[PDB]
Length: 50
Length: 53
Image (cartoon, rainbow over all chains, first blue to last red; front, top):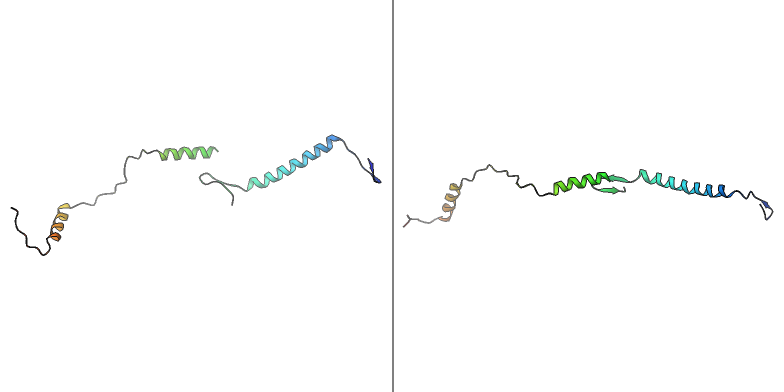
C-alpha cells in the first residue's frame, strides 16, 4: 500500500477480522472475570451487591 | 437456582397449616373457690348481710 508518501502492509482479510474478534473476546473475558467475583448470593436474601 | 427451589420447598412445607395445636404452657392452678370468696368479700364491703330466703 502506498499513500501520502507512506508505505503500508495492506493485510489479509482473515488476519484483520480474526484480530478484531480477538479484541472483542478479550474485552468480554476481562469484564466477565471482574464481575464474576463481585456479586454475593444469599439464598433467602437473593443476589446482593455490597 | 437449585438452592432457590429447595428453599421454596421448605417454605411451602412450613407454610402448610398443619400445626393443629398450641404451645400451652399451663400448670398454674385456678383455685376458683378462692376467687369466688374474694369477689363476694369485696362486693359486700361494709355491708351487713343476711341468710338466703
